[PDB]
Image (cartoon, rainbow over all chains, first blue to last red; front, side, top):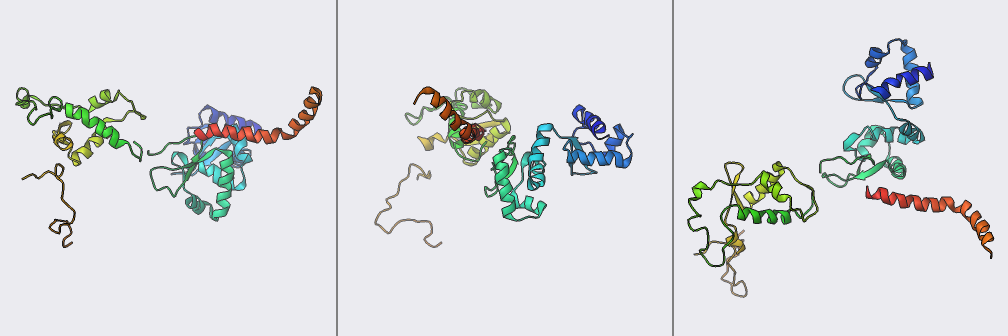
Length: 277
Length: 36
């Protein structure tokens, strides 16, 4: 019966719905009582009367009962937004770009942009710019914003040069760069005895905040370490152990780049680099 | 004019414009939605 088998076949949906994995085989598994065209003609109307839904993946076809507000909602949706919208909620947590959804619906740019404006009015979808190239405006629901992304923009250098400070502390005592030799003086007693680094500790150190951000994983902490490895501000020894490169002498014959200034005006005696390319 | 003709004239204005002001305040709610 339309209402009876609708509401009891939705009783498995609101009860469980076999998660999202429910296929027509799982229907027979629970309700096999209905004849083929019986359970089928009603289910087709359960999409027509918007009670359950179909999903296209892997083997067979998935199903679960749609909610009522989403039911009425997608009934309000246009014939475009029928496949467009209810396909975008199928575009899942990662959303989808446009002409790739055109390639699915086989339509022009105009006809899809207009239902993008209409669902824009719905505000159940939103413009989403992820890490990948911002020509996209991939569109996922406008209820969730999961993605792959720290953030792609700056003020990592800030928090870097912040941690570099404590890293300088991590090795010998503080700078003592006042006069030339004011270091540890044989490194306290036997720097051999000093095997030291922070790793996880930085987070206990990160507790200070004073900046707009969340915490960050020791893995990506190591990533932050990797640049000043490459920038040679620090040293990588025995994995999680680390050192300073005595960078500070930079911060403050000769072969250092800093502490060196050219004449570099008038006279033709210079060394440029490309005096021959 | 009296306060009655404002509670009546103005009333008619409101019965007419409640959708206009409704869209104003509604997009003003989209402001909250804009944030998220």
